[PDB]
Length: 141
Ligand SMILES: [Mg+2]
Image (cartoon, rainbow, N blue to C red; front, side):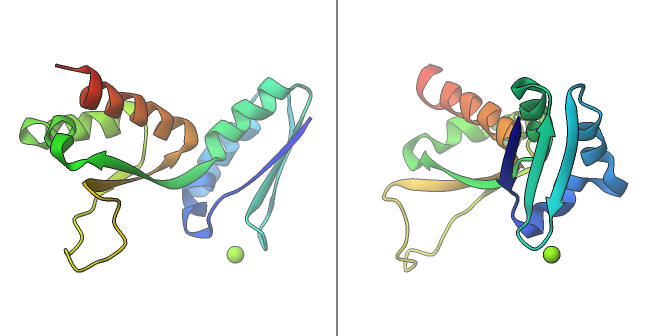
């Protein structure tokens, strides 16, 4: 069992972690045979005995910067009082950071009626953040 994914080069220090701390975790996953980074393509290859093990290792390393578009009319539901809810969401989810971006009205490329929330984190952490977003946006009354 072998999987491969690309981690953008500016996120590489998150994937590897301070003195390899993060990649060390992915390596010590039982069942993982090997993890190799092809630095000229920023591609991790993870080799291992079962799929679950290789996926568990991918889980630590698969950093991304993904944009979620949040309806402007609902933005406050996700930010909270005392910017506290958005901080809890980042903290619970496990993401590294969210940037909420307000672009000048002249800036043409904008989904209409939307505020970009740009998360940096593992794919799984962003998935966690997304459920909490949707919960506060659409569900919670
Ligand atoms: Mg390089």
